[PDB]
Length: 155
Image 1 (cartoon, rainbow, N blue to C red):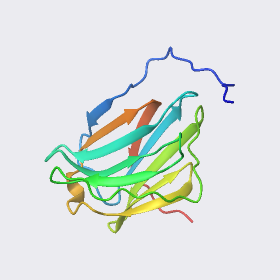
Image 2: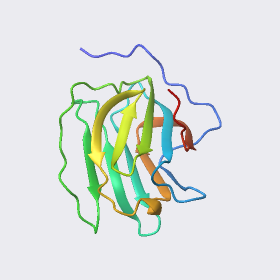
Image 3: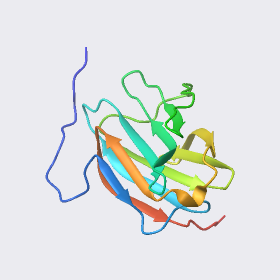
Image 4: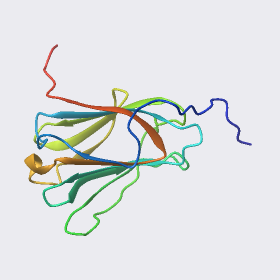
């Protein structure tokens, strides 16, 4: 038993996957890279490959999953895959919804929260943070627009 309530709509001038573009300048600590988009009603699963055009080295590779609802977080360095883990208190990602991934760098680890709801963390596997320049994104989701701002501290 599985049906669909929402319907997919395609007819607007915007980005598309696979999305492979580089940032005017190399990102790193203090910087905040967010990804505003929307999942498809019948979307299998998406993924975000963040590498450094410099040495095409994937510093962080977060590939979520809806089917089984398992979040995967690993890195690819020196043409080698680390250890993929799986353990989340809950899976926010949903088919046909608006999800926002915020990537903040505190020079201590790679943080990633969805819709302003911390999910999981991943230490800064990549030493050179000022190397990441190319942002690769693929999957069965719809990319609206990608923003990148320093991000002040108000509270």
